[PDB]
Length: 117
Length: 179
Ligand SMILES: CNc1ccccc1C(=O)O[C@H]1[C@@H](O)[C@H](n2cnc3c(=O)[nH]c(N)nc32)O[C@@H]1COP(=O)(O)OP(=O)(O)OP(=O)(O)O
Ligand SMILES: [Mn+2]
Ligand SMILES: [Mn+2]
Ligand SMILES: [Mn+2]
Image (cartoon, rainbow over all chains, first blue to last red):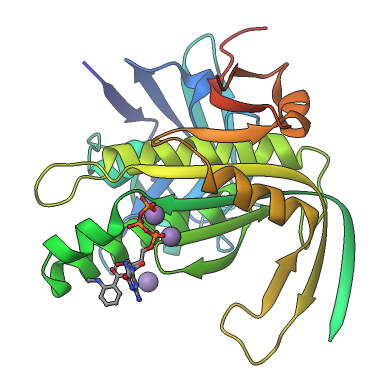
C-alpha cells in the first residue's frame, strides 16, 4: 500500500521550533518530489515547502527563512524544520507528492498549534 | 522592445493529446472545469519547482528554466519538472476516469527574452532552445518526453533515457535511483 504518515506536531508557543517528519512507503523518495502543505480552514491546503529529487528547495513567501525542508533517502523520509513559529502558522500539515496532491490522496497529517499553554 | 540574451536556458512545451476530440465530446462547462483543474495543478507545480511559465496557448503550456534567473542545473531542473508534469497528467482523471495524455518536448541552448508590457504573458522567450523544444513536442510520441542530443548529454548521468527508434532524439524515462 502507498502511504505517507506525518508526525512531529504538537503545541509550541510563539517563537518556538518544531520538526515535522513525513515517512513514505510504497515509493522511492530519491526519484520523487515532495512538498509540505498546511490547511488552516480559511482555505484548502496551500504548499509551504517543496523539495525536488535533485535537491532544489522552494518555500512559500510567508514561511521562507523560517522553515527548512530536507530529505533522508535511507529512512525514505522528508522533514520540515519549523523555526520562529507564529500564530499564523497554526494548521494541520501534510506531505504529498505532486501525483498525490492532484489525485487527492492525503495522509492524516500532523497538528501544529501556536499559542500559550 | 527590450531584448535580453541568455547563453544557457532550457525550454519545455507540453501539449494535450486528442484535445479536439476531448473538447468535442465534453460539455463546455465540464471542459472548463477540467482544464482549470489541470492548469491550476500545472501552475502550482511551476512555482513549486521555482521555474517560469512563459506561454499558455489553448492546450499548450510553455515552461522555461534559467530565465530570468540563471541556474547551473537549468536542464536538470526542467527535467524533474517535466517528470512531475507527466505524472500529474497521469494521475489527474476526468469525471470518466481517463488520464490526460500529453506530448512533452524539452530543449536546451541560448534564448532571447524581453518584456512586452501590454500582454498577459508579458515576458516573451524565443530563440534556438524554444524552436528546438517546439520541434521536440511536435514530433513526440504520446505520453513520452522527447529531447535532443544536447539535453541527453546534460541529463545522462542523473537520468535514464532511451534513444528514439538528420537528428537523433531521446525519451526521458526518469531519475536514476543510484549512479
Ligand atoms: C470544440 N472545440 C472548439 C470549439 C471552438 C473552437 C475551437 C475548438 C477546438 O477544439 O480547438 C482545438 C481544436 O479543435 C482546434 N481545431 C481542430 N480542428 C480545427 C479546424 O478544422 N479548424 C479550427 N479553426 N480549429 C480546429 O485546434 C485546437 C487543438 O489543436 P492541437 O493541434 O493541439 O490538436 P489536438 O486535437 O490536441 O491533437 P494532437 O495534439 O493530438 O495532435
Ligand atoms: Mn494537442
Ligand atoms: Mn486558471
Ligand atoms: Mn496544441
